[PDB]
Length: 138
Ligand SMILES: CO[C@@H]1[C@@H](n2cc(-c3ccc(Cl)c(F)c3F)nn2)[C@@H](O)[C@@H](CO)O[C@@H]1Cc1cn(C2(C)COC2)nn1
Image 1 (cartoon, rainbow, N blue to C red):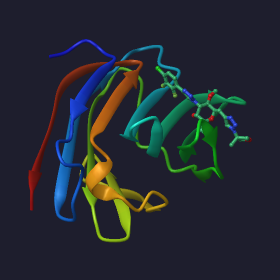
Image 2: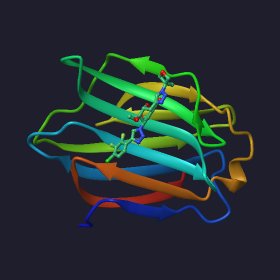
Image 3: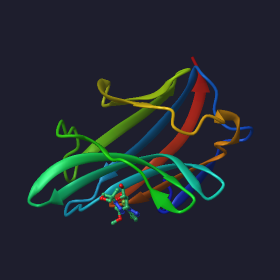
Image 4: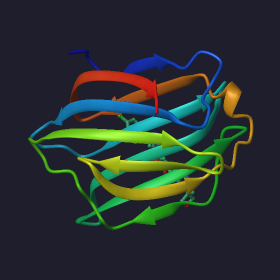
């Protein structure tokens, strides 16, 4: 176990068939979680569970380019629960990131940042106890 925020290096960036697995537990009064796949200061892929946006739960995904956020992609399917252990898996494919939570498909996010081999850090933050962050090739 690790204390957030945590940065996982992705040396040489990401590549298709890379599977990133984040294990932890959602804190009991959680408000937000964020994963940030970074290319320098740019955020290629921001994955942001919000537990109380206008008294709703929503997943917001986006990209930050030149310090500006782009167009949000939102999902109301919300597989997280306060207080519960989770597993987020991010599978890099040629054209998108695919996200599964607790072994159930959640969403896909098309690559806006094209230079996968420059997406060299994953930031993990928010209202979690982080157990582990690792990757393998499938
Ligand atoms: C309030 O800032 C969030 C921003 N954010 C979250 C965190 C964050 C920080 C720490 C933790 Cl621990 C954590 F879990 C976080 F999520 N940091 N930045 C992102 O989520 C962005 C995703 O579009 O939306 C907000 C900013 C925003 C949105 N938009 C629009 C595109 C314009 O109309 C919608 N303009 N600016």
